[PDB]
Every structure is written in structure tokens, then in C-alpha cells.
Image (spheres, rainbow, N blue to C red):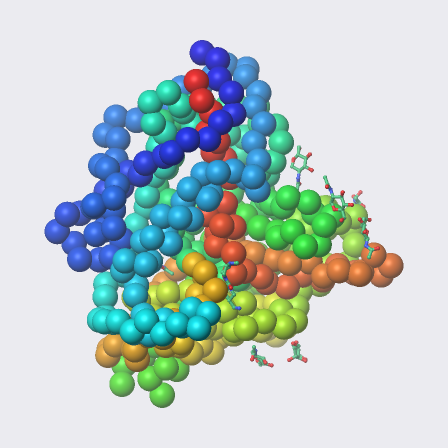
Length: 340
Ligand SMILES: CN1CCN(C(=O)N2C[C@H](CN)C[C@H](C(=O)Nc3ccc(Cl)c(F)c3)C2)CC1
Ligand SMILES: *[C@@H]1O[C@H](CO)[C@@H](O)[C@H](O)[C@H]1NC(C)=O
Ligand SMILES: *[C@@H]1O[C@H](CO)[C@@H](O)[C@H](O)[C@H]1NC(C)=O
Ligand SMILES: *[C@@H]1O[C@H](CO)[C@@H](O)[C@H](O)[C@H]1NC(C)=O
Ligand SMILES: *[C@@H]1O[C@H](CO)[C@@H](O)[C@H](O)[C@H]1NC(C)=O
Ligand SMILES: *[C@@H]1O[C@H](CO)[C@@H](O)[C@H](O)[C@H]1NC(C)=O
Ligand SMILES: *[C@@H]1O[C@H](CO)[C@@H](O)[C@H](O)[C@H]1NC(C)=O
Ligand SMILES: *[C@@H]1O[C@H](CO)[C@@H](O)[C@H](O)[C@H]1NC(C)=O
Ligand SMILES: *[C@@H]1O[C@H](CO)[C@@H](O)[C@H](O)[C@H]1NC(C)=O
Ligand SMILES: *[C@@H]1O[C@H](CO)[C@@H](O)[C@H](O)[C@H]1NC(C)=O
Ligand SMILES: *[C@@H]1O[C@H](CO)[C@@H](O)[C@H](O)[C@H]1NC(C)=O
Ligand SMILES: *[C@@H]1O[C@H](CO)[C@@H](O)[C@H](O)[C@H]1NC(C)=O
Ligand SMILES: *[C@@H]1O[C@H](CO)[C@@H](O)[C@H](O)[C@H]1NC(C)=O
């Protein structure tokens, strides 16, 4: 019953249905094992551990998989990679991320912080031990984190160094905000997302107050990104295979804290993407026919605070994204690998 921080090679578990053609099911059928049918965590009594979500290998462990997963599934007609043009087959596929678990091999375990207000760094008091993590959907997105877990109590602000403006801030919402995005049946690339103005605005209000506590009640200001390539300037995600690019100016720019209706963001489905796995562009074919719809829960926000504001009374925050390791860090933050 003693251990030390260490890294090893993990394996995955998921409930992939062997028959299903959906790319995540297929990727998990041949690369992951069946989920533990008999899990049991082991509370360690009055044991206090330290965690660090910004420096956790599990996150790089998951990243590598999703990159492998996307490489063998979601695959472009043409891939441009620093002066190369590999052409390929690019058939429309079935895409809907499932949860995947991360388990340790014999000789190690994962420590799971259960402080409902854990921020991801430092000390944790109620510490549990698990063999595998819970089911995590590997949802790829910028600006908004969708379909994830929620914070159990207060909205949590996660960062490696709040004081360093270069380090990303992950907001962990305690209440989700539904976001419905549709590309109507037959511009075929035109689409949009609908969001409750009231709900979203109340949540953003609350978020503002949280950041207030972390930044000496200094005026909090939200704005959209200042410069970017579209993947970052817009809220980007994949819905049923298609890459959606939505303009979130109406969430971070009306402030509005008579505005309380249904926010409607304009989006566009882009065949040509700047990849997240590695630098390069990938070009897909045009969209599939019929209404393409994905309703998702917004569960977190990726923010970047402005710099050089030290001499003012304001703090400016803009939605960020691009590095997916932060998206995985969004769910894995409470886990840590220790060798027995
Ligand atoms: C650093 N590391 C290595 C290479 N990367 C880049 O160069 N990126 C820059 C690029 C614009 N310049 C945006 C990229 C991005 O996020 N693409 C993206 C694609 C599809 C979806 Cl669905 C999505 F949500 C996002 C991030 C990845 C990060
Ligand atoms: C510690 O977390 C575990 C996980 O559910 C649970 O027993 C309870 O929330 C906490 N226990 C105590 C004694 O606080
Ligand atoms: C969410 O957390 C905030 C604190 O940031 C709190 O005021 C609010 O009541 C919480 N709401 C829910 C639904 O948990
Ligand atoms: C996280 O919590 C620890 C301990 O309470 C604290 O030292 C650290 O500053 C916190 N980080 C943030 C971003 O709140
Ligand atoms: C946090 O950022 C500030 C500003 O760059 C820096 O001076 C400080 O050393 C950072 N904290 C740590 C622990 O490095
Ligand atoms: C989502 O949007 C479409 C089109 O506006 C609508 O038909 C549907 O009822 C909305 N809600 C859900 C849960 O799909
Ligand atoms: C938006 O959510 C609020 C609760 O915050 C609710 O009163 C209202 O019915 C919702 N709006 C719509 C159009 O469903
Ligand atoms: C922020 O303002 C609130 C006012 O409700 C006050 O109670 C609190 O002490 C202030 N905190 C800081 C860090 O300025
Ligand atoms: C998003 O829409 C607003 C208008 O609502 C526009 O000013 C802005 O340029 C758009 N964003 C981008 C990156 O084009
Ligand atoms: C929103 O901010 C953007 C700056 O990127 C700009 O289009 C616009 O002036 C702002 N909104 C309003 C209502 O002025
Ligand atoms: C979120 O989950 C819903 C229900 O499982 C799904 O229909 C939707 O496609 C998911 N969103 C994304 C972006 O994958
Ligand atoms: C969206 O949120 C509701 C309530 O927070 C939850 O019951 C539901 O499972 C969430 N959807 C997904 C796809 O996780
Ligand atoms: C802004 O303030 C932080 C901490 O107060 C400091 O670490 C950082 O270097 C400052 N930035 C500039 C440009 O002075």
C-alpha cells in the first residue's frame, strides 16, 4: 500500500459494439478491450495526494490515440502536409464519439481526486484509487467543450498559471447549455446553431463572477478572438462527419449582462481544414445530403486572457482553442498514474 508518481503504458477500454460501423466503435473494437464489468474504487483513508493536470502523461496518452483514431477513420481526399499531396479515398463515414476509458497495467493504479472543488493542480484530500478511468468521449472542438462532464458544485477555473496570460484557462461549467446545430436539407454549406439566450447569458454571468474572484473583482470583459485562422476564430467541431465552423460573436460580444431570446449563430461546413493532429491542411468532400443535426451540451469554455492589461482596471477574455490536449485535460484532470 505504498507508491510513487510514475508513467507507464496504458491500455483502453470501451463498450464498442462489434457490429457498428461508426468509426469510434471500430477503432475501439480493435484497439481497446471490453470495459471492466466489475469496477471498484478503493478509498484511501486520510491520504493526501498532489495532482497536476497541466503536466499529466495520461493526457498525452489519450492524445496519441485520438490522433490515431482520426487517422484511420476520418480521412481526407487530399492531405497537404508541408509540401506533399497524398491523395486518397474519402468516403462519407459514420461518426459519433463514444466514451473510452484509460486503465493501468498490472503494477500501477490511477489515483482519482474526489474533491468536488478540485481545480486540477496541487493537493487533494479525498483520494480514491482506480484501475480504469470513467468513460470519456474524445470530442474534438475549439472554443467550447461539448458533451463532457460538469463540475459538481461551483464553476471551476482551471489553469497552469492564472497570472501568466499565455496559459490557457478552462472553465468548468456546473450547468450545461444545450447547443443545437443544424445544416438543413436541400448553399449546402450553410448552417447554424441555436442556443437559449437566457440560459447562456446567465451562465456567462456566473462565469464572470467566478473570474471576478480570481482577479481581484477587476472588471471582466469578454471579446472574440483577435487574429486566428478560422479554427480558432470560430467555434469548430465535427458533426456526423462534417466540420462545422460557427461564429460565436453573439455569445462573447453582446455582453448583454431586451436580449433574452434564441441566439442563432451562423455556421459554415468547410471541406478544407487546418488540422489539429499536426500542421497541415486536409480537404474533404462536400457534405452529405439531408438534415445534419447535432444537439450537444456545452460543458466548458476555453479562454485566453489578454496581456498588457496590468495597468488598467479590466481583464479581457477571448475564447481559444487549437491544442486538443486541453480538451482531454478537461476530463482527465482528476486522474493520476502512480506505480505501486
Ligand atoms: C500545435 N498543434 C500542432 C498542430 N496544430 C495546429 O497547427 N493548429 C492550427 C490550426 C489553424 N492554424 C487550427 C488547429 C485546429 O484546431 N484544427 C481543428 C480541426 C478540426 C476541428 Cl473539428 C477542430 F476543432 C480544430 C490547431 C494543432 C496543434
Ligand atoms: C469522498 O469521495 C467518495 C467518492 O464518492 C465518497 O465516499 C464521498 O464523496 C467522500 N467521502 C467522505 C468521507 O467525505
Ligand atoms: C454554479 O456555480 C455558481 C458559482 O460559480 C453558483 O453560484 C451556482 O449556484 C451554481 N449553479 C448550479 C446549477 O450548480
Ligand atoms: C488550485 O488550487 C491550489 C490549492 O488550493 C492553489 O495553490 C492554486 O493556485 C489553484 N489554482 C487555480 C488556477 O485556482
Ligand atoms: C506565473 O506567471 C508569471 C508571469 O509570467 C510568472 O512571473 C510566474 O513565475 C509564473 N508562475 C510560476 C510558478 O512559474
Ligand atoms: C434543434 O433544431 C431543429 C431545427 O431548428 C429543431 O427541429 C429541433 O426541435 C431542435 N431541438 C432538438 C432537440 O433537436
Ligand atoms: C431558456 O432557459 C430558461 C431558463 O434559464 C427558460 O426559462 C426558458 O424557457 C428557455 N427558453 C426557451 C426558448 O426554451
Ligand atoms: C470582491 O467583491 C466582493 C463584493 O461582493 C467582496 O465581498 C470581496 O471581498 C471582493 N474580493 C476581492 C478579492 O476583491
Ligand atoms: C462573426 O460575425 C460578426 C458579425 O456578427 C463579424 O463581425 C465577424 O467578423 C465574424 N467573425 C469572423 C471571424 O469573420
Ligand atoms: C463585437 O465585437 C466585434 C469586434 O470583433 C465588432 O464586430 C462589433 O463592433 C462588436 N459588437 C457591436 C454590437 O458593436
Ligand atoms: C453530443 O452528444 C449527442 C448525443 O449523444 C450527439 O448527438 C452529438 O453529436 C454530440 N456532439 C458532438 C459534437 O459530437
Ligand atoms: C446534457 O445535460 C443533461 C443535464 O445536464 C444531461 O442529463 C445529459 O446527459 C447531457 N447530454 C449528454 C449527451 O451528455
Ligand atoms: C503583469 O503582471 C504580472 C503579475 O502581476 C507579471 O508577472 C507580468 O510580468 C506583468 N506583465 C507586464 C507586461 O508587465
